[PDB]
Length: 139
Ligand SMILES: NC(=O)[C@H]1CCCN(C(=O)Cc2ncc3ccc(Br)cn23)C1
Ligand SMILES: [Zn+2]
Image (cartoon, rainbow, N blue to C red):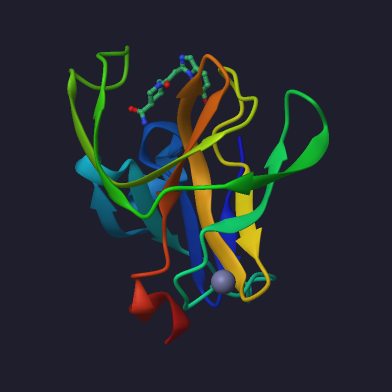
């Protein structure tokens, strides 16, 4: 679990969005596993606007942060799950690092700010949904 809180927005994994997220919907994209909802309070986070390919993510299943080298956002095949049919997920970045079911929502950061959130993984890989192209989160 986990979310990004920036301005009057909350960014979560679309498959973990709550009834309240859907009632306050701003934007969602199944192909990215992202949903953005509106908030009443001002958020604590800031968003990176960069092309970094290294950073640090939070791994809830280890209660620890780990450094990672990750691929640029791209279209990557994701096998069927209870939440989605077998499909290509867009704007996804992969890295070698531990993740297991339950780690979705952990934040990836570089020196410029928040880069994305954990969205998939397995077998020593971790995959992050990128948010750096969503320039409207800043206004
Ligand atoms: N983005 C998606 O389509 C995910 C929706 C939830 C389901 N998806 C998964 O990957 C579930 C899953 N099985 C093994 C692992 C290991 C690490 C992590 Br993080 C998640 N994992 C796929
Ligand atoms: Zn950066």
